[PDB]
C-alpha cells in the first residue's frame, strides 16, 4: 500500500509541479505577450491611422 | 482601439461616399432638367403622342 501510494504520489506531485511552473510561466509569458501585442497594435494603429 | 479607428474610417468613408453620390445625383438631375428645359414640353409631347 505504502509502495503503490508512494509512487503514485510521486508521479502525481510531479504533474502538480509541472502544472505549477506551467501556470506561473504561462502567467508571465502571457503578460509579456500582452505588452508586446499592446505596443505592436499601438504603433500599428498609429501608422495605419 | 481598433474598433474605434474602424469607426473613424467608417464615418469618414461613408460621408465621402454619400457626398459623392449626392453630387453626382446633382449633376444628373441638373442634366435632365437642362434637357427638359432645352427640348421643351412639346418635344417629349411629340415623342409621347
Image (cartoon, coloured by chain):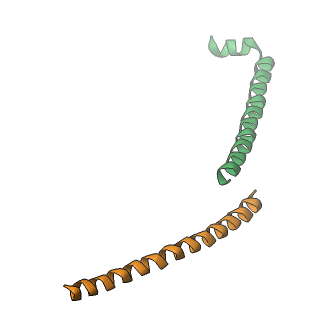
Chain colours: A orange, B green
Query: Of A48 and A7, which appears nearest the observer?
Result: A7
Left or right placement of residue A11 versus residue B26 in this view: left
Residue at 77 percent across and 19 percent down: it is: B39
Q: Residue at x 76, y 19 (%)?
A: B36
**Residue B10 percent across, percent down from the top left:** 68, 45
**Residue shown at 69%/49% (left/top)?**
B4
Q: Residue drawn at (76%, 36%), measured in percent from left and top?
A: B19
> Toward which corner of the image does residue A7 lie, by quadrant?
bottom left
The x and y percentages for residue A1 are: 19, 84
**Could you say where residue B34 lies in the image, as x and y percent from the top left?**
80, 23
Q: Quadrant of the C terminus of chain B?
A: top right
Count the labels in the image. Answer: 0
* Camera-side residue of B41 and B30: B30
Q: Nearer the viewer, residue B49 or B36?
A: B36
Tell me the quarter of the picture where residue B44 sits: top right
Return the residue found at the far front: A2
Residue A46 picture location, percent across and down = 76, 60
* Position of A1 relative to A32 (above/below): below
Say left or right for B22 vs A34: right
Amino acid at each position: 500500500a505504502v509502495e503503490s501510494t508512494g509512487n503514485a504520489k510521486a508521479e502525481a506531485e510531479s504533474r502538480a509541479e509541472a502544472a505549477r511552473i506551467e501556470g506561473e510561466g504561462s502567467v508571465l509569458q502571457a503578460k509579456l505577450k500582452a505588452q508586446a501585442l499592446a505596443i505592436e497594435t499601438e504603433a500599428e494603429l498609429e501608422r495605419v491611422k | 482601439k481598433v474598433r474605434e479607428m474602424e469607426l473613424i474610417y467608417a464615418r469618414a468613408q461613408l460621408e465621402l461616399e454619400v457626398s459623392k453620390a449626392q453630387q453626382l445625383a446633382n449633376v444628373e438631375a441638373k442634366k435632365f432638367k437642362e434637357m427638359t428645359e432645352a427640348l421643351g414640353p412639346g418635344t417629349i409631347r411629340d415623342l409621347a403622342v
